Length: 129
Ligand SMILES: Cc1cn([C@H]2C[C@H](OP(=O)(O)O)[C@@H](COP(=O)(O)O)O2)c(=O)[nH]c1=O
Image (cartoon, rainbow, N blue to C red; front, top):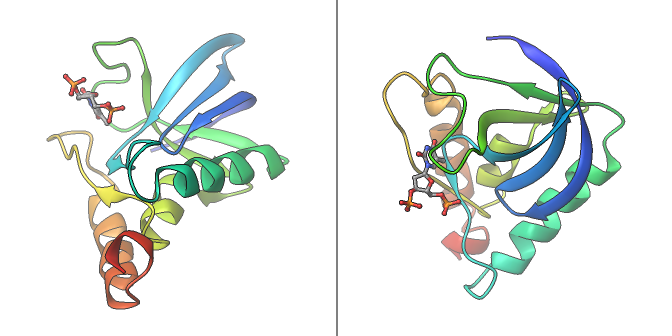
């Protein structure tokens, strides 16, 4: 896979962010994760976590997987990086997201994220507390 440039337009919530990609505004949905809803336990903490990671980043990058690049809502499907750190992975490592929505052909980082989830669960972090 390849990292491509983007710039933050604005934080939205734990697993969606609005970025400028190839000069066009897009909502991106983070591949391979599910964050709780804002009104569910750890929803607000997941939003806050993603917000801080993307807002504090000097360099945002988008990495598409090998399959579908947009979902049925027109959201971009990607791995998002903040100064070389994957937001998708970081959410799961902190117990603020579950590995989820693992579709065949867009699952390159599945084992990386499952390892993060196993570490978060072992540490009883957040959703695993
Ligand atoms: C993460 C992801 C979500 N989706 C769709 C499936 C879900 O459909 P439904 O809306 O019909 O439930 C929805 C979940 O996203 P959210 O968790 O943002 O709601 O997004 C994909 O099609 N591909 C994906 O990779």
